[PDB]
Length: 145
Length: 145
Length: 141
Length: 141
Ligand code: HEM
Ligand code: HEM
Ligand code: HEM
Ligand code: HEM
Image (cartoon, rainbow over all chains, first blue to last red; front, side):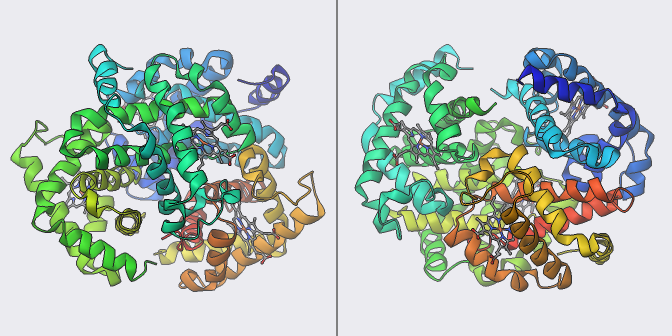
């Protein structure tokens, strides 16, 4: 994964991340901004506007959950793959979410991280976090092969 | 990845595969069909028109060169990380090629074989190539990740 | 946006597809689903065994669909739109899939027209199908 | 095409962008070279090292076009059309990168304009760039 000096950077930084609320807004931000995504989330309720989504209570709790996986992936960078085993099965082989979309969410996450933390999330941090989401793109993708 | 019936199916086929002209046609094709691939093949000569690189000698020659290196791994479908370790390297740190183009030439090769083989190259058949081309691809992309 | 060669290529090729289209669109999909399984969730209704006249009657209006688009090459924006909205607003089809269909369609023309599938053709038709996909996404709302 | 609501939403957000167009240009520029190293290859003659003369020129020339785009949205086909000639025949940029700058911007806005960067706005800058991007890649096809 990452030069252990690099790890200490993605790590020292998650320390100050309010995973909860990033979580809500991430999934929302994705749902609003990559409409097709919705389709997999249509048991959630009404997602017909911005507000619909950003407000919807389901979106919110399903987001705390989806940063948890990260907050969690973070603990175990060195073997993302393994740590992700199950979720990787869940998405691929009975949800059937094309892996392009682990990226998209990957990225939106970044975008929400940059909003939360300003120019404090420098590009040297971000260059890091973008592997972290590239890698969490990689573990969730696996069972496609 | 590759069931007992799969791992053979392909190589009983591959056996009848004219490995040599395919690559030269495959190649000009990535090149004719997808102009932005020409940046890396600058120093190759006239490419300015399909004819050019449908008859360009280095193309012709790098076509096969690739295929061998392809068709060797066709015979190695267990360890591709391995077979393609320092091809993955040349293509990442050196040539610096965006992983998608793998998947391009990939597909493209599949079209090649499916011109050379007609009705004979069934939906069964290629469905199996799909995850070889794609197989070979994450291999070539490893020494980024 | 295209050429004149291009259009003259799409055409001839698709005239040498001709009355096959329906039987080819057919094939298109079978390869598609069979190669990239995740295209089968867009059809939970479908019988997906070889032949299923569900499949067959579909490969058609895809081919009737395209035949319409080959015809109106000089303006795909308009003639298609009706189809675009559906494939997005309704269906909500992760744009990624049209890459997987184009390719299938070709591989399908690929063994059905070798002494026809010269580079420039493969360059034109792909290129064509690019615009078709890039219409059926035009409405990314 | 872009919904009226979006159109309005850029102008605002990029209105904010203000006299800062070409700092944010150099900032998206540089977030992209690190988080996507590959993309450096296209910019060989540079001295990429932080805050480098020439990146800052690119910083601004880019962001100035974007600006000119934010001008006439109804015709992005045309007011960028010169750049589509360059970016594809002279440079030949692999499309993938276009997203990567896109993404680069999206962030950079957020780093500096949290409060304007609402979701319906983020949705918007994007639909704008995805827009932008295609224009810049018309000629591959
Ligand atoms: C890297 C990104 C993702 C991570 C880390 C992730 C992780 C998770 C987690 C922790 C759960 C809950 C486990 C459970 O309830 O069984 C879940 C469920 C789910 N995920 Fe994601 N997921 C990701 C991306 C996606 C994407 C992109 C989609 C759709 C495009 C998606 C669709 C779903 C659905 C439909 C469920 C179940 C919803 C439900 O139970 O009501 N996931 N995923
Ligand atoms: C699809 C599977 C691919 C295979 C099997 C493959 C294989 C190879 C091989 C075997 C070599 C020769 C190694 C040597 O120098 O001794 C090579 C070099 C090279 N590869 Fe590929 N490669 C693939 C994909 C690509 C793609 C997609 C591109 C760009 C679009 C690319 C660009 C190049 C270039 C520019 C060279 C150096 C040739 C020269 O000296 O001009 N490769 N590759
Ligand atoms: C080459 C581009 C495509 C064309 C020309 C096309 C054409 C059409 C047409 C005309 C219809 C409905 C009309 C009728 O039944 O009378 C339709 C329906 C549909 N298409 Fe395709 N489509 C394309 C791409 C795709 C792709 C890539 C997918 C997913 C992989 C897809 C999945 C569907 C679905 C889920 C429906 C509605 C289900 C139904 O008919 O019962 N389409 N398409
Ligand atoms: C938002 C997308 C982009 C915009 C708005 C944009 C804007 C511009 C403009 C207006 C120019 C010309 C300035 C001049 O005439 O000297 C330029 C030059 C150039 N662009 Fe882009 N660009 C974009 C994306 C990209 C990307 C992603 C790459 C590659 C990663 C790229 C590669 C280049 C190169 C190599 C030059 C030549 C500069 C030189 O060598 O002097 N462009 N860009």
